[PDB]
Amino acid sequence: EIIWESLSVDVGSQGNPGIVEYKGVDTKTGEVLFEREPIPIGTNNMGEFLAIVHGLRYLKERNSRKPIYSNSQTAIKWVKDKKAKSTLVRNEETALIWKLVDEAEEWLNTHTYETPILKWQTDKWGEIKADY
Amino acid sequence: EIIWESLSVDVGSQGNPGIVEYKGVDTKTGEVLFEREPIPIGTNNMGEFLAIVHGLRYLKERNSRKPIYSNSQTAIKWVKDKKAKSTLVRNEETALIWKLVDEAEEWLNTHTYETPILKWQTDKWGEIKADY
DNA sequence: CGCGAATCGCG
DNA sequence: CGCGAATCGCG
């Protein structure tokens, strides 16, 4: 079952592709540990991929042993693969989200980390904490 | 139902990826109208994509009004899209099949053709004629 | 509404 | 055996 001493990372979109944001919350207290303000164009999967890698950087900085939960099979797999296999066109309007994704991949390719990245089982455990 | 005055195009593989060949046969008489000798490395889908575009070039040359049948949803869609969305790595060993695919796409991009490309319904009509 | 992973026919 | 199109959870 559930490690409550953990970080849950969630993405917020509505229109997909469209404005995307994300945050990292303490799984137990719901305390917001980091948040990214709205990016004008991205996809759910790119935003959740960024949320996971930001969570990794955040916990590594803090020397934390906590795991990360995500409800996204896709973003967990992209993090494992060190590759975000997004279909989002690369153009002037998507340049920011692609720059951030590209740089998150480079981070993954050049650092080690011990944080377990675990799948949040929404059908058994309810909504990921503080789900947008 | 079935237009018997037509061309059926089929691919032959075994190992996929692996040696690939294809041919075009008269749907009715089974007469072999063209055949490509074995290409040492390709995939089923790339071979069937080539078989369809070869069939188009063959019939156009002959001023023929005949349709082409294929049992491949994938190769029909790649021909429609004028793009073969193969995952086959581009390396020294796959250079020949990729050169042929690239040149078949260019053909599609630079010619018009009236040949209908129709899906062969194997579950109702049995095996595509002269199936390898 | 769209995004992508996980889940048939074909040789 | 693998190749790709057609066919769930998530916000």
Image: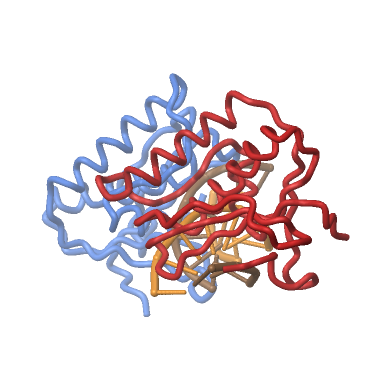
Chain colours: A blue, B red, C brown, D orange
Task: Return the residue nearer the eye: A66 or A109.
Answer: A109
Q: Position of residue A72 (x, y in %)?
A: 44, 58
Task: Return the residue nearer the eye: A45 or A12.
Answer: A45
Q: Is residue A108 above or below residue B64?
A: below
Q: Position of residue B124 (x, y in %)?
A: 80, 72
Task: Return the residue nearer the eye: B30 or B1.
Answer: B30
Q: In the figure, is residue B14 to the left or right of A27?
A: right
Q: Is residue A79 above or below residue A123?
A: above
The residue depicted at 64 percent of the width and 49 percent of the height is: B76
Q: Is residue B26 visible?
A: yes
The residue depicted at 40 percent of the width and 68 percent of the height is: B15
Q: Position of residue C1 (x, y in %)?
A: 68, 42
What quarter of the picture does the N terminus of chain B occupy?
Answer: bottom right
Task: Return the residue nearer the eye: A123 or B19.
Answer: B19
Q: In the figure, is residue B87 to the left or right of A18?
A: left
Name the residue at the bottom extreme. Answer: A1
Q: In the figure, is residue B2 to the left or right of A2?
A: right
What quarter of the picture does the C terminus of chain B occupy?
Answer: bottom right
Q: Is residue A129 visible?
A: no
The residue depicted at 44 percent of the width and 39 percent of the height is: A21
Q: Position of residue A75 (x, y in %)?
A: 39, 54
Q: How many marks?
A: 0
The residue depicted at 54 percent of the width and 34 percent of the height is: A18
Name the residue at the right extreme. Answer: B1
